Image: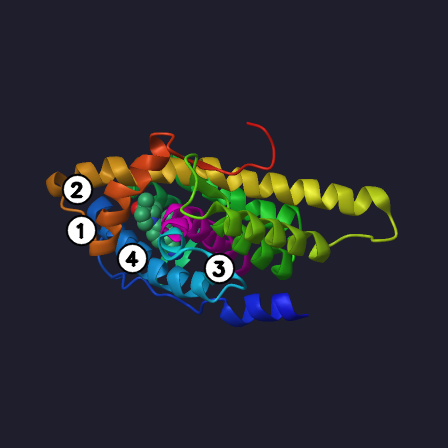
């Protein structure tokens, strides 16, 4: 049980946004609160990642980058799970103090993207994704997007990803006395992982675009946000850093 012992043991607790629920819903407040939530969620992903099995084989700057490139898809992924498990995918459960209803979806101007993220949530229920399946997939997300140019030491990354792909394959919810079953379960879960990437890309696009006009619209971006968004995110949007897909796109 050792691998999943780890994952569950290091799975972060509740991160609040700091949001002031008892004021008017508005774009500037909704998005200033998400940027503080993203900033906090980051700090936790950092410690979560660093405690992952085998993670510190990676070169130190690879570690940071990997985290930076994966940070949005992971947040989104875990977010969707919170929304699955807390509200049964009706609303987006960013935080206990930041739960997006339809109305906030519109006011945040992220309706198109919230829709996708919510669809994602619903897949968890449709597919009856087990909590165990969720953690393994989420851990695997960390290792699903790299510079095409390669990492400072790619050898150890491939070894981890391979090993993390292996661990998910053991734990899939399936009839082991039936070929088609586990075969089928894997395919589904791989597709689901793949489906996280286009959504992350949309959020990147939006946050980046948003950052550029942040001075105008007075949406506050934290230290590490602006650092990531202006430096790492554009590499992804420029096609320098690409997601590792299971299936061809
Ligand atoms: C997508 C996202 C967050 N933000 C932060 C950056 C963004 C593009 O504005 C994006 C919508 C922030 C926090 C959680 C959490 N938990 C999250 F899932």
Crowding at mark 3 (Cα within 10 Å: few <14, some 14-19, many 20+): some
- The numbered mark, 1 or 4, whose residue comes first in the sequence reads 4
- The numbered mark, 2 or 3, whose residue comes first in the sequence reads 3
Crowding at mark 4 (Cα within 10 Å: few <14, some 14-19, many 20+): some
- The residue that appears at 55% across and 36% down in the rendered structure is 245
Q: Which residue is mark 3?
A: 57
Q: Are marks 1 and 2 in contact (CB under 8 Å)?
A: yes
Report the disc number at residue 220.
1
Q: CA distance from mark 1 to mark 2?
A: 7 Å
Judging depth in this view, the residue of 216 and 162 nearest the camera is: 162
Q: Is mark 4 within 8 Å of ligand 1?
A: yes
Q: CA distance from mark 4 to mark 3?
A: 26 Å
Q: Which residue is mark 4?
A: 39
Name the secondary structure under disc 2.
helix
Name the secondary structure under disc 1.
loop
Q: CA distance from mark 3 to mark 1?
A: 36 Å
Query: Is 81 colored magenta in this rendering?
Result: yes
């Amino acid at each position: 049980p050792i691998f999943l012992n780890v994952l569950e043991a290091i799975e972060p607790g509740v991160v609040c946004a700091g949001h002031d629920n008892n004021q008017p819903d508005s774009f500037a407040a909704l998005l200033s609160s998400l940027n503080e939530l993203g900033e906090r969620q980051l700090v936790h992903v950092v410690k979560w990642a660093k405690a992952l099995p085998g993670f510190r084989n990676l070169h130190v700057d690879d570690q940071m980058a990997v985290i930076q490139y994966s940070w949005m898809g992971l947040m989104v992924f875990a977010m969707g799970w919170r929304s699955f498990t807390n509200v049964n995918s009706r609303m987006l459960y960013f935080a206990p103090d930041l739960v997006f209803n339809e109305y906030r979806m519109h006011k945040s101007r992220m309706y198109s993207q919230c829709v996708r993220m919510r669809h994602l949530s619903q897949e968890f229920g449709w597919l009856q994704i087990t909590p165990q399946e969720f953690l393994c997939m989420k851990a695997l997300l960390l290792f699903s997007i790299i510079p095409v140019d390669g990492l400072k030491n790619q050898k150890f990354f491939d070894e981890l990803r391979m090993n993390y792909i292996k661990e998910l394959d053991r734990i899939i919810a399936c009839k082991r006395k039936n070929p088609t079953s586990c075969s089928r379960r894997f395919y589904q879960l791989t597709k689901l992982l793949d489906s996280v990437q286009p959504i992350a890309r949309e959020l990147h696009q939006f946050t980046f675009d948003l950052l550029i006009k942040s001075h105008m619209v007075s949406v506050d971006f934290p230290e590490m946000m602006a650092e990531i968004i202006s430096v790492q995110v554009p590499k992804i949007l420029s096609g320098k850093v690409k997601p590792i897909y299971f299936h061809t796109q």
